[PDB]
Image (cartoon, helix red, strand yellow):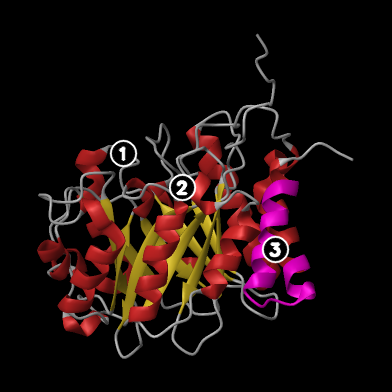
Amino acid sequence: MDASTLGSFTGGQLRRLGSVAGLSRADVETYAQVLTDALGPVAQRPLSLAPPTRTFLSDDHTPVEFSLSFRPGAAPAMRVLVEPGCGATSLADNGRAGLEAVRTMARRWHFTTDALDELLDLFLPPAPQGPLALWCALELRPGGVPGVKVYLNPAVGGEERSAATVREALRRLGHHQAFDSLPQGSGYPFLALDLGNWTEPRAKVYLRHDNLTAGRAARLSRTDSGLVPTAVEGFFRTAAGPGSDAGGLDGRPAQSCHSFTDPGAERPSGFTLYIPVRDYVRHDGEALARASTVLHHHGMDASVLHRALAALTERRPEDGVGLIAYLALAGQRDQPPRVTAYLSSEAYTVRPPVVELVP
């Protein structure tokens, strides 16, 4: 019928993945509409056109990514990550469009944005530097009222100003000198806020880790942020396969996230390690096999993740790479660890046209 658009294609993925995650037809319809509205003008962009901006949200510049988070005894939790300002003619207008999208969501669900407002001069200046201005992740909760997380760029004024930007953000969010509790890293790729019916900020600091080793990974967190060193080393080795025991992971950098949630607290209560598994496998069959091992090690079934990949695309996992972009092990104080698979939309990753060569 009609040519596929970013909206129709990513919407189809949201619907099929949402059903795999056990969401109702009603909730899936609600969230498909939320994603279309979040994409704004680019939702109508035909997939036959080049990607609208070189968004760094995914390798092929699709401005949508999905995730499924597995907790023992819990239904799978689905998120969608979007860049609402995708297709703006400048990073400044990208940020403004991103902020408008978050405020529209706030007027709909009436979550508090005071914590975001406290940060906007730091993260949305004029002449911003890449690679992002504002991304939004929506947790697709039963009942149609999502969790909203906003991702901002500590390097917006240059990498040299990243550390000072994170320290000032945490101070403004009532976390004093929490910056000094963070482990050594190579960079600060994101600061994120979890927004809801709370005014108490939930602040997340991301660190880049170049050439990470299993031992160094074991030292990024303390017991009181939900993971134990042996679980972190086991996960590192399972996820990384050949990147393991070779002088440090040798593909794109690993990341950690440090969650500050207790009011006034100078120490994080949550820790996540992200491994870019797509750089360390022959194909998505191997990524799926490693994800299945991690899930089994944390007491969870993996059949939903097998259905999730088929929901994304009809492609055999073994016939490409990148459908599973990252795997993560997520700890929170006094909670069972969570395993998360980040799933690529691949809206711009197409089989070339079939035209047989006949001599």
Residue 249 lies, in percent from the top left, at: 20, 50
Residue 121 lies, in percent from the top left, at: 40, 49
Q: CA distance from mark 3 to mark 1?
A: 39 Å
Residue at the image point whose x is 27% and y is 82% from the top: 226
- SS of the residue under disc 1: loop
Q: Which residue is mark 2?
A: 322
Residue 315 lies, in percent from the top left, at: 60, 48
User: Residue farthest to the front?
Assistant: 359
Q: Judge left or right: residue 6 versus residue 339.
A: right
**Mark 3 crowd level (few <14, some 14–19, many ≥20, 10 Å Cα):** some
Q: Amino acid at mark 1?
A: Gly
Q: Amino acid at mark 3?
A: Arg
Q: Which residue is mark 1?
A: 157
Single out the mark in the foreground, 1 or 2.
2
Q: Nearer the viewer, residue 1 or 272?
A: 1
Circle 3/circle 1 CB separation < 8 Å = no
Query: Is residue 206 visible from the viewing direction of this image?
Result: no
Residue segment shown in magenta: 8-29
User: Residue farthest to the right?
Assistant: 1
Residue at the image point whose x is 51% and y is 86% from the top: 74
> Sequence-wise, which precedes: disc 2 or disc 3?
3
> Sequence-wise, which precedes: disc 1 or disc 2?
1
Q: CA distance from mark 2 to mark 3?
A: 19 Å
